[PDB]
Structure formats: structure tokens, C-alpha cells
Image 1: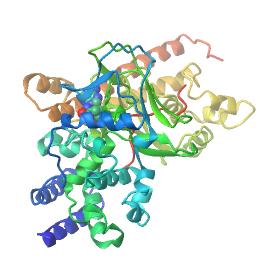
Image 2: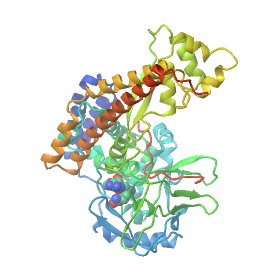
Image 3: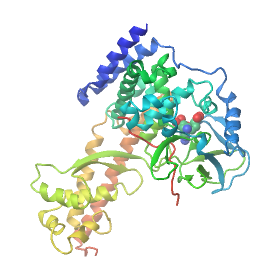
Length: 481
Length: 15
Ligand SMILES: Nc1ncnc2c1ncn2[C@@H]1O[C@H](C[C@@H](N)CC[C@H](N)C(=O)O)[C@@H](O)[C@H]1O
């Protein structure tokens, strides 16, 4: 059996190290990788370390451990909520902006704490651990999880045992995402995780610096999937104790807060060396305490946080645009973009909340549709730099003609992107209404629905802007500034 | 504003 896992992981490492076989066969590659991972998983015994008690049986030890090290432990309790899972619930009225939660650095798991642990020797030798702090945190979790006397045991024993990241999806649940933007990141996540597991499985067996690790005796795919999912759904960027650099950290107790819409109210206090959270809003006794995770899209929430957020005012879709080398005005357009700090080709974003395009995308689209005369005015003369400075400003167009052209292009491109999906918006709503689905299936279908709804709104907003600027052109309105 | 805002589950590169 040990030699059989070596053969399967070696086969997995080679299949996952191969280049992409073209986007037309990425689903076949995904299923091929799934088959080998599931064969390895069926031959392994799941998580190497499991705890006898229930998850809530260890929360009192988390509170005692956090209290002994200076963290806030009063005013809230752990509750298993249906929608979000476990989270914090207020036991007293908490006013907005009240500093109610603080976690000193001594409780955190960091890349620095990983470097000084039993993972130290292997960390100083493996180039992937040195370059990827998130992967370093994942192995930091695993090594301490398998260490019964670890300082962070109260935190690890209260972590979830499974997640709703796409790594846990069934094949037919991912299949809903066919022909979407997000599935390619799902493909990459699965392939990367499989390649990393096979890579480190071989590294741990061949490197003498890993002999003292518990992973030397047991390191299953389930371990790695749980570790990277624990990190991607919970990790944070904090300043170093010096304050001159940034590092990645797991923040116990505080990271039990679930997400709602708002503003980030959690910051690191460098003078007291602790993470501080003020109340995002008023929380009455008996209400769940929420925080705002960040301005991430539902694609990022699903893939990296394992949930879909219905009230995501920061949702967005990607749109790749670039000046064609076949364009007669390519050189001038690329130079105007260069002077504006914009690459010639890039992946932009289309947002659901108006305005649909950012200042950087507006500036790109303006230059993309400029005439030679307009490009010259942004390249030559004492006003050229002033014209560059306003390229991202909606109130200062290059010309009414330039606006009509760019909004017509965006309307056509967004409408073309909508035609590349295998289902329509009405079909997705019918599936959600008429079929009984798992949580993970609903995440996938809502994700593909959300992509098209953002594209549909971009079509409507671009069509509206096209008519507005066409009116200014027909009425010969004076250009602003 | 917050000198060091903390983003819960900040997205990192795994490639
Ligand atoms: N608004 C939400 N709706 C659904 N699930 C959520 C929401 N906010 C957070 N979550 C879940 O909570 C995870 C993040 C955790 N750090 C928060 C505590 C987590 N609920 C736990 O039981 O440990 C995410 O991966 C989600 O599974």
C-alpha cells in the first residue's frame, strides 16, 4: 500500500504538471484529475488526525486559551447558525464602533510562527514554501494539528472538518459551471491542489528535513484539502511585528465572525500588537455578530471562501480587452495607455453596482476608440498630459463621438459574452425554483446566474450611455472643460 | 481610517 500511493501520487504529479491541454479539453482533464484524486482518497483513511469530541465541545477551551493570552472573551457566545454555520452571537447589547473583540499576536498562526515550528527545517529548504506563505500556513496547520501538545490546539480543535470550497464539490455540481468564467478558476484550484499534494507528498518522503514532521508517517489528500481550504477561507494579511512588511496569519476567535455587507471594521493595532475589531453595526443581545470580509466578488467568495453571498454589492465579472496589433493606430494607442499607466492588454472588471466600469476601464475604452487626431492630442503639446489626467473621469469625455463609440463597443461585447453561456438567465431561475438542490449546487447555479445578470445589466447601462452621448452629439452640446 | 485593515479570507495566489 505505501508503494501504491507512491505510484498514484507520482502519476498525479505528472498529470497535474502537464500544460493545459487547451480550454476545449479542460473539463476532460478535470475529470481525469478527479478520477485519480478520488482513487487516492478511497485508498486513504481521510484526515490523519480526528478529535473525539464534537466541535462545540472544544469552544470552552478556545475561550479559556484566548483569555489566558489577553483576548476578549466576554459579551458573545458560539452558536451553530443554519445559514452561515458556527458564528458569534452577542450576549449583551453592542453599539456600533465599540471595540468589542481583540486578539493579541501571541494567539495568531503566522508564516513567522510556521518558520519557527517543526516545519522550520523543511521551510528553509523548499522553494515553494518560501515563496507561498499561504501554503506554508497550510502545512503549519497540519503539523500543529498532528501535535497533541501544540500551543494552537484549542484553535485547531474548533476549526471545521469540511468546507464548501469547490474542492469538496461533486462532479455534477461543478458541471453546472460549464461555459462560465468561474469554472476555469475552479479547474485551476483543483489542479493546483492536486499537484501540490503530490509534490509535497514526494518532498516529505525524500527530504531529511521532514523526518521530525508527523506528516512523514501520515499525509493524506484529505489532510491537504482540509488545510488549504482552512487557509483560503480564513487567512488574513497583517503587518509584521516590525511594521515594515506584511505577512499572512490565521486569527483565532475573531475569524468565527460570519460575513455581511458593510465596511471593514477590523484593523491591526501595532502599538498594542493585537488585532482589533469594532462593531460594524448595533448588535442587540441574541443577534449574530457579523463583520465585513471585504469587497470580494461572489466568484471569489465561492471559490476561496466557500459561500455565495446574495447581498453582494461588490459583485463583478471579468472582461479581457486589448489593443489589437492589427490596428493601424496600435503604436499611438499603446503609447497613450503607457503614459496613463494602463497596459495594452489586461483583464478588466464589469461591476453590478453602477458605474459598471472603473476609471481604468473607461480610460482604456476611450483610447481604444480614439481617432488619430484625438490620439495626437493626448501625445503632443502643452495640454497632452492634462488630457491624460482626465481619461478616467466620466465628466470629461474626449468627444461625444468617442463616447458613443466606446459604449457601443461595450454593449456589443457584453451582449456577445452573454451568448457564450450554455444556459439563459430565465433557465437558471427556473432550475433554482423548480429543482431541490444542495447548498453546493445552489452556489454553482447562482454563480453562473450572477455572471449573466452582471453582463445583462452592463448591456443595459452601455445602451443607456450610448443614447445619452448620442443626444449630446446631435444637440452639439459644448464639451466639458 | 484603519492603518492596517484586516480582510477576512483575503484572496491569495495558489498557482
Ligand atoms: N454570510 C455567509 N453566508 C454563508 N456562509 C458564510 C457567511 N459568512 C461566512 N460564512 C461561512 O463561514 C466561513 C468563514 C469562517 N471563518 C467563519 C466561521 C465559520 N462559519 C465556522 O463555522 O467556522 C466561510 O467559509 C463560510 O462557510
